[PDB]
Length: 193
Length: 193
Ligand SMILES: [Ca+2]
Ligand SMILES: [Ca+2]
Image 1 (tube, rainbow over the protein chains, first blue to last red):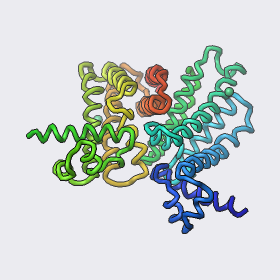
Image 2: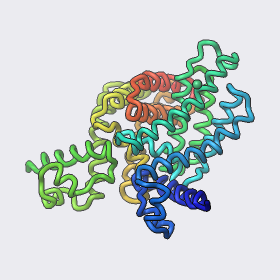
Image 3: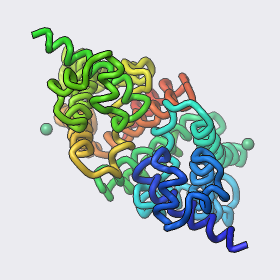
């Protein structure tokens, strides 16, 4: 079952490629060529390019979650966990796992005008991410760490916005100042949203 | 010189197509087929697909500027002009000229990992937009409408971030609540950044 290793090789290379070229740059044939494999050998892991595209998206999300959310679980729900998650996500955006930055953020713009199975998977991922942030904001109000009338969705909007702007600045401008601005924007989100 | 009209037809259809498919979905052959023209007839306006791609980006930016910035010039520089520009840009994002939303925002994610002439043009456009916002923030401090130690680049970061998040929410989620959140995020940007 060194298949599991081969699968990881495929998905790993696909995430790298897709982070700069887009998910639609991902075909069975492209990956066979990149890894000096037969198309047959790729096809036994992933039947269609859409399956490969979705599995690559999922893999990248798993790697992100392991770097960003899992380390934060050593903190209690609420502001403690939220601050940890946000510090980790900023870190991940300023030093991405993939050469083209955050694949989740890029897939968002690539697929929002592309109705179908891949876009539905992008929506699913973004939904889980937003919920992880929202749960800790909600917990923080519940625990009295934020005021009773605090607007959870406003703060969430602004926190996600900071991430999107950080990724754009890093990828387009190589602007390393954006991270400190994202950090400040996240604190400001917590102060009256 | 009904060529000028033909050019507008080409660029118009190209902006529509690119807003959902990306700028890399733009070829001479695609547009010839879309408009029932010869490739020859397209090629006399735009020699290469990169020229066509850049001209389409520019056209879309011109249309945006005419809807968003020009109407705001009836206001004095500073907060008056800034609020008008931001209200217009929010309006444009909730009711876009193109079916796939803001082309400038999409090109940003499409081309940041694609070094070359198109990406350089995307950078140029985004630079002009950021400067239009920055000039009015700077004017507002200069006029004493914002406090003396107000951080112009923080506010700018957060204002641009709100636009990026609004476009993502509109395009992916059809979430019409995002506009009111963008509006609130822009006011909050002006309050201590
Ligand atoms: Ca929940
Ligand atoms: Ca200037």
